[PDB]
Amino acid sequence: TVPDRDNDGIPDSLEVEGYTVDVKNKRTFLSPWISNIHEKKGLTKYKSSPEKWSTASDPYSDFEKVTGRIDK
Amino acid sequence: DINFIKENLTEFQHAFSLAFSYYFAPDHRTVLELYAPDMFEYMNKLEKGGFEKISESLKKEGV
Ligand SMILES: [Ca+2]
Ligand SMILES: [Ca+2]
């Protein structure tokens, strides 16, 4: 498998080097930052720490904060 | 046709190598499955036995 230290759902290399979230038909997919695809659509580029479940130490993980699976 | 295939084969070479690196870097393989779902199928057929057949067709000529 691919490593995930903090167990939030994003792999470590994506957290260290960059990732984003795109929606293709009606399904969202967490993908690494490609500056050709994701920069034309105006997506945001995120980085976070690979060993904290929540990088800002609040009770919401990085995966929930970027994918909308959060308290609204 | 022949003219496009003979002047700029480095671009098709670049396309295949970039698809190869997207297929085998394990952190982002699903990028290829999402944004190019038939290049993913091409590389998946090529990995599940096509590489073996190209190796055999070269090793037969090698002896
Ligand atoms: Ca992680
Ligand atoms: Ca994290």
Image (cartoon, rainbow, N blue to C red):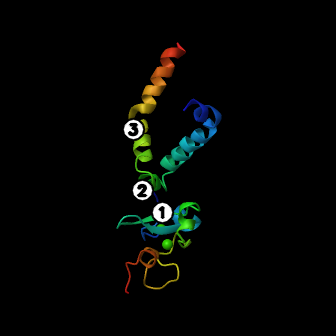
Give the total number of marks visible in the rendering: 3
Find residue B12 and report its horizontal and vertical position in percent. Answer: 57, 40
Disc 2 with disc 3 on a shared chain? yes
Whole-number angstrom distance, CA of label 1 to CA of label 2: 10 Å
Find residue B8 and report its horizontal and vertical position in percent. Answer: 63, 37
Q: For residue A11, say whether it is visible.
A: no
Q: Residue at x 43, y 71 (%)?
A: A8
Residue B27 vertical position relative to residue B20 in the rendered view, above or below: below
Q: Identify the disc placed on residue B34.
A: 2
Tell me whether the residue at label 1 lies in contact with that at label 2, contact meaning CB atoms closer than 8 angstroms.
yes
Provide the residue designation for mark 3: B45
* Of residues A44 and A8, the one drawn nearer to the viewer in this rendering: A44
Q: Which SS class for mark 1?
A: strand
Disc 1 with disc 2 on a shared chain? no
Query: Which quarter of the picture shows residue A17?
Result: bottom right
Tell me whether the residue at label 3 lies in contact with that at label 1, contact meaning CB atoms closer than 8 angstroms.
no
Mark 2 is surrounded, within 10 Å at the Cα level, by few (under 14), some (14 to 19) or many (20 or more) other residues, namely some
Chain at numbered mark 2: B
Chain at numbered mark 3: B
Q: Which kind of residue does numbered mark 2 sit on?
A: Leu
Residue B14 vertical position relative to residue A22 in the rendered view, above or below: above
Q: Residue at x 42, y 41 (%)?
A: B42
Mark 1 is surrounded, within 10 Å at the Cα level, by few (under 14), some (14 to 19) or many (20 or more) other residues, namely many
Chain at numbered mark 1: A
Q: Which SS class for mark 2?
A: helix
Provide the residue designation for mark 1: A31
B57 displayed left or right of A25: right
Mark 1 or 2: in front is 2
Q: For residue B12, say whether it is visible.
A: yes
Of labels 2 and 3, earlier in sequence is 2
Q: Which residue is drawn at 51% across and 15% down?
A: B61
Find residue A11 and report its horizontal and vertical position in percent. Answer: 48, 63
